[PDB]
Image (cartoon, rainbow over all chains, first blue to last red; front, side):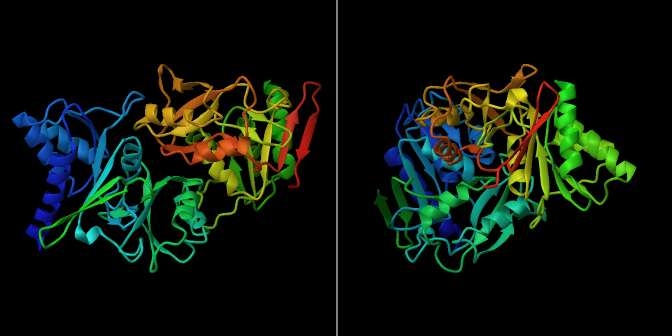
Amino acid sequence: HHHHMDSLKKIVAYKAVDEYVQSNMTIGLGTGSTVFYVLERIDNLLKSGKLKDVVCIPTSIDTELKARKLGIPLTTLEKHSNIDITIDGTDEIDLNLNLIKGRGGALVREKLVASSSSLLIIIGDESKLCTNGLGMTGAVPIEILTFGYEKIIENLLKIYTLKGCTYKIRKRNGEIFITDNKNYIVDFFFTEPIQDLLETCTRIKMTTGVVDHGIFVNMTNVALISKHDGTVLTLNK
Amino acid sequence: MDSLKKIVAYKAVDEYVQSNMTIGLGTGSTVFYVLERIDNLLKSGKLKDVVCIPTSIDTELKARKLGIPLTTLEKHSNIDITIDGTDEIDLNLNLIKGRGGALVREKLVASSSSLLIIIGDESKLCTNGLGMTGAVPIEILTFGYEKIIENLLKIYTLKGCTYKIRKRNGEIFITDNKNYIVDFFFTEPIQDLLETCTRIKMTTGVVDHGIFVNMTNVALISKHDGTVLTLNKKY
């Protein structure tokens, strides 16, 4: 139900802005179709004067372009930067508030900005909420260098918890997808939930050729999940 | 130093490089004569059916121009032998590399190799601790780089350091992987070397770093007296 899903996205997005974003804040902006309504709302409130002195840091080039068209003030991640709040979406989230992210290709700058913020708010419709184990609804992305990427993938497959996976290099329009950071992404697929989750993150990240991966562990402070019945579930660390 | 570079480069090729090998090609001014010499031997017929993988675009072009057969690092490539230079090497045969900008590809190529051979002159051999002779390079994203640096300075072993973003021709150097490099400088030897390695690598926004631990099998060190010291780690 497409307008319905849109409305559900809208609801959580408006809520994150209305309830958590304040004037004179620096705000990290996530990526994707849910976050769209975050940009909409922030621009709305800024134009009305309900909000003032709000500057944003974008997690992708897509998000930067959209924000700039709207006229939302933007800055950049410097040594002095500290972000009050980042609002982003996710591809999956469990009841521990651990996330699978990156299916829109923005995972690396999403993690950097989110780790650089006092508060990470993750927003989603109820299909993102996965209560029977992470990693089974789709791609678990890993950003890797273009140079020698197949060798990097073979090395990833040694990791004991990934040895059973299938995988596909990410493609758009029959071309290998290139990230903002000029890397490639390999999607690993799991038929059972990802085992020893934190050890997996660590072994992926320690891999030569790996830039980062789409698993965010112990980073989410708040989640707002919009349910079909009208409700919004708030989850806190 | 150049004839000292020539001698270790020729020794390295002549004594380890065989026909039918896949060869990792390093980067820089010593490795220029590895290239030179591999050309010579394929062309003479002394060597054959040797194919190469370059650790930089710079090395690729020079080799492509010499007529060295080149291939890419594919799913189950094994490199028989990589030959590279180094900025520092100690007697554990641990290295500091990347002062020419190529640390990341160098590292991946070398780790994909059955044997890593490090060549250099006397000045590279560091017997009083690693990391004091110049840049210790950390490859990082261009996005939010100032913030990645700040997060690197949280590491207890880096906290003290002088550091400088890497420039060349008045501009921030851009690596073959389209990243930046931040150089760290130490006045004492790097502490807790492996821990430091790990904490850098685990840093969000870090691609890799130029500390190469337990990866070198053989080093050839050209001496001022013209001889070459060969170091060999079985371990």
